[PDB]
Image (cartoon, rainbow, N blue to C red; front, top):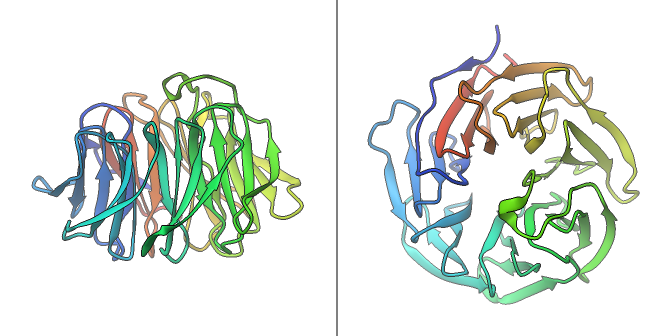
Length: 305
C-alpha cells in the first residue's frame, strides 16, 4: 500500500515555511513568515497552539524542549518548548539568518546568514561561539554531522562546504550550486542533510538528483534519481534509522528512496505544484510532514509500509 497523502491545510502566510516533529513525535511543529510557531496535534487540528516568536521567522529548530528561531530582528533566539518561555538570545548577525539547526544531542546550534557567515553557539552558554568564514554570498542551509566532527553548509556562492568544527577550517568545497547574490534569487535552497547515525554519507540535492558523498574522503558515492523528478530538488531529509531518504522538489514532488538498495519507496505529487521547503521524518513511525512555499502543511502516512 502506498503512502497516504492527507489533504494539505493552511499553516502560515505565504513564504518560506519549515516543519519538524516535536520531541515526542505526537505533534507537528511549523514556523513561517508570519512569525508564529504552530503546534499541531495532526492535520485535523483546527486550533493549534501558537508561539509568537517575532514579526517574521526565517527558520526554526527544535530539540529537547528548546525552540531556536531566526527572526527578522537579525537574532538567533531561544524559547522553551512547548511552553514558549523566552530563554534569551544566542547570537546576532548584521543581516537576517536563513537557517538554524541543532546538532545531534541538542547542545549546539549552527546558523547561517546573508552576511555570509556561519556561527556555532553553545545552547547553554551563548558566550561559547565559533565563526566559520569563507563563503562569498548568503548562506542558505546547514547540517550537522551526527558525530559532531563536521558541519556542512550550502551557499548562494555556488558551493557546498564541509567545515571541521574544532578549528573552523574548510575540509572540502564542492561547486555544485548555481551562483546568485540574494537568497530570493536562489534556484534551490539546497537543504542538504547528513546521514543520521554513522554520518557516513552527506546527501546534497543538486538539479534533479540527490548526490551522496562519503565523509572524510569527500568522494562521490552515487546519485539517487527518478524519472518522475522534472524540476530541481530543494530539500532532503533522512529517516531516523539512516536507511531511507526523502526529497522535495520545487514543483511539489516528494519522493522516498531506500538508500542501501536505491529502490524508490514512494512518490507524492503536490496538488498545486508548490515548492517543498520543509520536510521532516517522524522520530519513530513511517510518517513524513512537509510544508510548501505557500505556507501550507501536509502529512504522509504509512511511508515505507
